[PDB]
Image (cartoon, coloured by chain):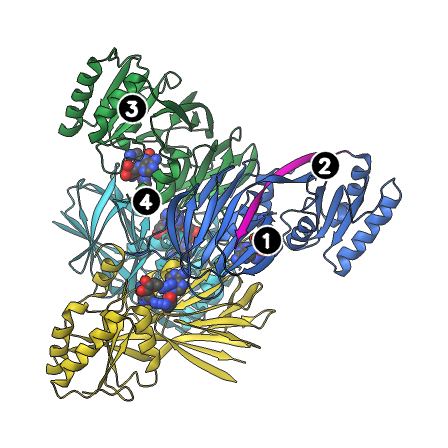
Chain colours: A blue, B green, C cyan, D yellow
Amino acid sequence: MKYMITSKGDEKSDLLRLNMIAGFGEYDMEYDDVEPEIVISIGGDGTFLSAFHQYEERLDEIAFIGIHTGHLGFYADWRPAEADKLVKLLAKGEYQKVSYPLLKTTVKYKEATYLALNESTVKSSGGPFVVDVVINDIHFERFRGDGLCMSTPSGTTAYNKSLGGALMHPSIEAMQLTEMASINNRVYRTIGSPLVFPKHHVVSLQPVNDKDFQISVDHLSILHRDVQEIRYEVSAKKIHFARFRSFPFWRRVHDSFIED
Amino acid sequence: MKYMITSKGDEKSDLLRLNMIAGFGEYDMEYDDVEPEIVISIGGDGTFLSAFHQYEERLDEIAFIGIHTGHLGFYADWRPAEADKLVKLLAKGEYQKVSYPLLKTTVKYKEATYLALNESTVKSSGGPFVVDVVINDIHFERFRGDGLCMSTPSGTTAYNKSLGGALMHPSIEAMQLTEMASINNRVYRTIGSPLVFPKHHVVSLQPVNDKDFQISVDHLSILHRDVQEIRYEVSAKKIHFARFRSFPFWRRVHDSFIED
Amino acid sequence: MKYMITSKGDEKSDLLRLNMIAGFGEYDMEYDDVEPEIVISIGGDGTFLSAFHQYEERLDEIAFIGIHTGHLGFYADWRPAEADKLVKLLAKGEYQKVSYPLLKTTVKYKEATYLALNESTVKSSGGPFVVDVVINDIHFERFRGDGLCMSTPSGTTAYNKSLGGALMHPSIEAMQLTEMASINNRVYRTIGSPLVFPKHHVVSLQPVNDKDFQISVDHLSILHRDVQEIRYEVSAKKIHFARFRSFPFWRRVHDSFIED
Amino acid sequence: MKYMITSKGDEKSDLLRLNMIAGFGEYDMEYDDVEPEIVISIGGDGTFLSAFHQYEERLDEIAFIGIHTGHLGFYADWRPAEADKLVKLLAKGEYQKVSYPLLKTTVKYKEATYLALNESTVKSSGGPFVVDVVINDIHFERFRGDGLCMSTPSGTTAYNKSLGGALMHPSIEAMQLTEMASINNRVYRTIGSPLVFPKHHVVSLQPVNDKDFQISVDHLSILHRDVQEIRYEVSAKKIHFARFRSFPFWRRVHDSFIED
Ligand SMILES: [N-]=[N+]=NC[C@H]1O[C@@H](n2cnc3c(N)ncnc32)[C@H](O)[C@@H]1O
Ligand SMILES: [N-]=[N+]=NC[C@H]1O[C@@H](n2cnc3c(N)ncnc32)[C@H](O)[C@@H]1O
Ligand SMILES: [N-]=[N+]=NC[C@H]1O[C@@H](n2cnc3c(N)ncnc32)[C@H](O)[C@@H]1O
Ligand SMILES: [N-]=[N+]=NC[C@H]1O[C@@H](n2cnc3c(N)ncnc32)[C@H](O)[C@@H]1O
Ligand SMILES: [N-]=[N+]=NC[C@H]1O[C@@H](n2cnc3c(N)ncnc32)[C@H](O)[C@@H]1O
Ligand SMILES: [N-]=[N+]=NC[C@H]1O[C@@H](n2cnc3c(N)ncnc32)[C@H](O)[C@@H]1O
Ligand SMILES: [N-]=[N+]=NC[C@H]1O[C@@H](n2cnc3c(N)ncnc32)[C@H](O)[C@@H]1O
Ligand SMILES: [N-]=[N+]=NC[C@H]1O[C@@H](n2cnc3c(N)ncnc32)[C@H](O)[C@@H]1O
């Protein structure tokens, strides 16, 4: 199986990458960073996020595996000390594929579409942020505040969590919208609560005054001008993970937030 | 079709019930509060909750309809002034069935099982509340605080919402666990965030010291003694609603929380 | 100086108490649990709370000191291993007095008044909790939910904190009101935010329907019937601590919540 | 008494300003926008904020009055229809002065100091925001998240409120620090809770990596580079309001958030 290895780029990760490549050379495994079938990310979640976006055009033909040489490393399944065992199991091909839902963001001015593994957020390009929130064509609320965050299930443990959102098991095909510092008084009103949307539900954001927004997709933050609308929906595309052992989402959550 | 009508029991609701019964008499519709196929609740959500629990043994053979003579009336689809039109449409049989997921609660000492339309909560029988939270057999956290709330999708707009939980579209077969005043310090740690569980996931609560708990299921609150565990899962059973017109969940939410 | 020592009552604490008493016997220090000038609490915050309430009638003539043989021990200034040094310093009389504000609760039916070091809360005697919140005679809100919590500054790190309240430095003579699971929809509205009141401000709770409430003052929970109103204000009374060394409130907070 | 009038600048406000000036001309009142003793702001809170900052160098010699021609208008005491009565009372000099505490922000690179009526916030100049929070020289926490907000008492109803902060009566000389989307996991830890600091307490923010920050003071947002630290304390300066009638803070809060 063709494979490639991304590295955090520090001494630890680069060296681990070289040793794994050496180990793969001992098997019938070809290194290909153009059309790999397996992508190994060595680092933290930032590194993993980069790996995903590097191959967001071949998500259907790739299974990802993360090795934790970072700090938290939520998307990682392996410790550096287990790298050799990983090489072996990957060789023998003893693994099952697991899929997590992704978030599709469409920005219309022309249209640009982005794919997110964690979340997509919107803020003002400086100045007051005000947007009408439209759900399946029904006007739901006019949001005034710092911004909004739309999260995938696996992303609910990231930015979403910090914003008071619920943690959502990845087997649920959904997206979750959370508020950033909503204004609520006699005249201005938002739902307040995070909202969880099923697949096939469309959430659209529509400018009220200012049409310039800072839009983020995972680690990438882009300024969009003359925006007509931002549209969120659960992507038809899924990220696939290669699992060689049981590591339940809730245990992953426990280890990352309660105690490791 | 056999039908029955529950009433809030005030002047307004009783009279509306009598007029509807009269209207039904003009059709080939038999009133039967033993084995009805349609249950009409006239009142608020409290009244609707009572109706559901009165027939929780025949949920598969019943479609519910709510008329709003209460204050908020979230589960209601009709205003009193539309009662006549409702009678007519019910007669002609022009309606489609819609299903919402329910929550199963099992209390083991012997075992008692309850079914919830909104939520099930647990608190201490007076004194400190401490329980181990076990998800699919994995020990997730030890919860210290006032109590916990497990909500259905349609219940997420109720108690769940007040506790900071996410609002969850009823098409998502899930349950959501929220905290009540969790203690979090150097020594005590909880996830904090609401947790959303898919169908077939089991959340079990296990006593640490005190074994006596006050357990609520919707409007019903019962004291259980010598409790060994409380087990939550998404019920295989669903409540069925009779819909004669489009009234999307998110519009229902908008009307109840943003503006009517 | 007359002194008394309260003990958690476990093996560790009782023995520590005996050794300290022995050490005090070597000085001109008389043990008196009737009219002591110094009260030493050996245990956790629960033990300290008990000590305070045991002498809430002589708060003006007493300085408290806590020794930590409990788990968290927020009000404690000493570790068991330092007991000998404490005995010595207490003997030589090398210490300065520090005062924290207290909360006065008045319950009218006849009137009963309670004094709180941490907080006073109100909940329903079973059933729905609804009260009108009146601030300095002006009707502020009608609260529907689980209950309310009124906290002292030093109490803001306790129950108050779990309810989303702000942490408040004890030098600020104030009380803070937090909500428990307030209902907020189209028809029901509360402020949501914690409220911080200065000295001489009076917050009164007035029943809307049910007149029976469960009222807590620190560790004590009492059911009151035929309640006409509950009145909160910053007490004119203060608790005095004996400080032999610098241990700033914010460091106390850091040690208890961030890292020890 | 010398006076000046700021205007929102719309048709309504400008015309109201002209009529008031005409009314003042009928008395011995001189219009002076250089060294006025009374500053009347006609508009919303944004307009009022601008008025305050226009004369932040003469806060000791000025009493402010707001007229509400805006939307919410929290700092306003008057409706446009009462302008004539205001002119009269201002003439006869029938009013009492009321003072609210202010927030001092010091930015060191050289030093710049700003004065805030509502709040001062800090965010990253793009990229991750990380700062060490130092309280009175003691290292309290390392904050990772979107940013921080330090609010005056009267400012607690603004940005502070949206961030989950407590509402604080203006008679309390304090400042309140709230978090924006703090990261909290196994490795990263913040207090979470808003913090309320008394006068003479100093809160300092110190860069960990990036030294560039976006710093806001009320409506003004400035990018600072090569920042060594940001220092917050309760200002020795106070804003003075001219009150011609009783309008308690808590009633002001009720009217702005509960019902007008
Ligand atoms: N800001 N930020 N990101 C830093 C934290 O987010 C973590 N992170 C990124 N993605 C996730 C994620 N999906 N779940 C939990 N934590 C995550 C990353 O590892 C850092 O600990
Ligand atoms: N790992 N990493 N970096 C990208 C992630 O940063 C996360 N992030 C950014 N800001 C915050 C934040 N304030 N809290 C938690 N996570 C955050 C977000 O989830 C992005 O996917
Ligand atoms: N406490 N309580 N219940 C009172 C409010 O809860 C409302 N309620 C009950 N069930 C729901 C519900 N599912 N969604 C929203 N509100 C609900 C009920 O109508 C009252 O307005
Ligand atoms: N309608 N009704 N009564 C039953 C509902 O009361 C709701 N409830 C009880 N306490 C609260 C509460 N504090 N906030 C919101 N809802 C609440 C809960 O959802 C029950 O299903
Ligand atoms: N529930 N409860 N109480 C248990 C926790 O509250 C702690 N506690 C009591 N009073 C305070 C307090 N004032 N500040 C912080 N923690 C406190 C006590 O030590 C336990 O850790
Ligand atoms: N130590 N102790 N026991 C009494 C304290 O318990 C605290 N307490 C009770 N319930 C909670 C709670 N849910 N969270 C935090 N603290 C709590 C409250 O502050 C009382 O003063
Ligand atoms: N974002 N923003 N500001 C808009 C809202 O904040 C309001 N505002 C400004 N200052 C305060 C304030 N101090 N209290 C309450 N609301 C305030 C202003 O009137 C707008 O309604
Ligand atoms: N009026 N006005 N504009 C300035 C105020 O905007 C307020 N503000 C900015 N963002 C928010 C926000 N997200 N929520 C509430 N208030 C906000 C803040 O209090 C400033 O003083």
Viewer-side label of 4, 2: 4
| Camera-side residue of B227 and A39 | A39
Screen quadrant of the N terminus of chain C = bottom left
Circle 3 residue: B51
> Dot 1 corresponds to which residue?
A218
User: In this orientation, which residue lies closer to the viewer: D234 or C259?
Assistant: D234
The reply to whether dot 1 and dot 3 touch (C-beta < 8 Å) is no
Q: Position of residue D142 (x, y in %)?
A: 54, 64
The chain containing the residue under callout 4 comes to B
Q: Chain of mark 1?
A: A
Residue position for label 2: A244
Q: Which residue is mark 4?
A: B257
Asked if one can make out residue D195 in the rendered structure from this viewpoint, the answer is no
Q: Earlier in the sequence, mark 1 or mark 2?
A: 1
Q: Chain of mark 3?
A: B
Q: Earlier in the sequence, mark 4 or mark 3?
A: 3
Disc 1 crowd rating (10 Å Cα; few below 14, some 14-19, many 20+) is many
**Ligand 2 within 8 angstroms of badge 1 C-beta:** yes
**Mark 4 residue element:** helix
Question: Which residue is depicted at the point 88% across and 45% down?
Answer: A25
Q: CA distance from mark 1 to mark 2?
A: 26 Å
Residue type pointed to by label 4 = Phe
Question: In the figure, C187 relative to C84: above or below?
Answer: above
Q: Callout 2: helix, strand or loop?
A: loop
